[PDB]
Length: 252
Length: 252
Ligand SMILES: NC(=O)CC[C@@H](N)C(=O)O
Ligand SMILES: NC(=O)CC[C@@H](N)C(=O)O
Image (cartoon, rainbow over all chains, first blue to last red; front, side, top):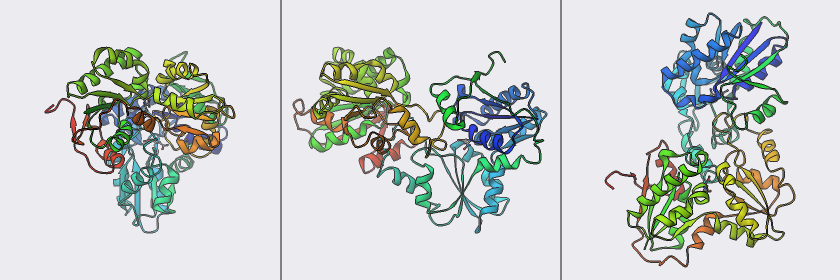
């Protein structure tokens, strides 16, 4: 069968790797909407229109299911997607909430997400409806202004502290909605102390087991709506080798 | 006297601190053009028009000299600024080149700069006219697409390696035009091995000694063209305390 996967960037290539490795024969089409790259800032409805278009493009590429590996899109576009694309649609939020609810002990769990994903309340609601005291904070948006220059040393593990304030000693499991410097993973586990961090990518990939008929030609096709700067090198580093990419709407 | 300092962001607050500390009485007006925050991408002439406007705003605020702490602006706008603002204008490139030329031993020196600053050839020319074999590379622009998630561990010190390839064992001094994850400072010195990294901020601040009449009321005024998200917190962390900021063109 053929799996379609989309994301606003190259982050979805992680989930895509989990899947390709677990589902050996399955065919895969990837769409990274690099042309509109900063999704997480835009309004709910723009997130929805963008998603509908990328999911429509994957559908017209003959795919059987659609995995939206983007937190923000998953948070606002899932319903609309399911209702308009006539295929099974899967997001990265529910397998993470499940994995969080499961892995916890004290049911006090934190979520570091994009200001737009944190704003939807999707994780919050889903965690609470699982009997959880949720501690959620938005991704710190620093790079636009400042560089990792000021933000190095003192200030890096002072921004962490201040940001993961409420989490201090109440949570034991964390959903890493998204990490952006200085709130990297190694920096946050060292402040929170060793906590069980959800692997949303393995949870998602694993989660499609019942829907996936593990059959096909192991084909992979990469598509992006903007052939951005170092994208071609990012691919070689995430997938392990060089994979040829196409501009979404080229030969088609 | 009054010193005007501008930057596209909050990075100039570092130079501003060096200056305030070295020139105890000097008055200071700061303008961060946060509204148009990603300068380093825009064309030369747009960089020049933007600069002219910020320098004009500082001039109309009665300042005596203007420090452009931005590499990109310094690289393309200095001439035009001097020619149109009737005051002494100082950039961050020449004090760094001087400090590089001086500190070297083998006159083989590298420059990690923004794609636009690296493109101007300003450092290159100035280093070469000082008898230097320059090794320059542009800042890797990753955050738009990818997050520091993929880029953590293996890939962080693999992007470094690949990027600081030509520098390997030929340079002994580096001008850190600008650092953006994963090419942080601690990550780059560990690959290049211990090399003498130029402190462009202390070089610039020190460099204004002959022009500065160390007199005034030690006043500080912060202005930004966009009262961005976590800007107010970035200030408390760089300067050490809370400083009230104004929107450029508010009360004026
Ligand atoms: N794989 C991911 O972490 C996706 C993150 C992305 N959904 C975000 O909101 O930043
Ligand atoms: N202080 C600085 O490093 C300024 C850097 C800034 N000029 C840049 O080009 O990114």
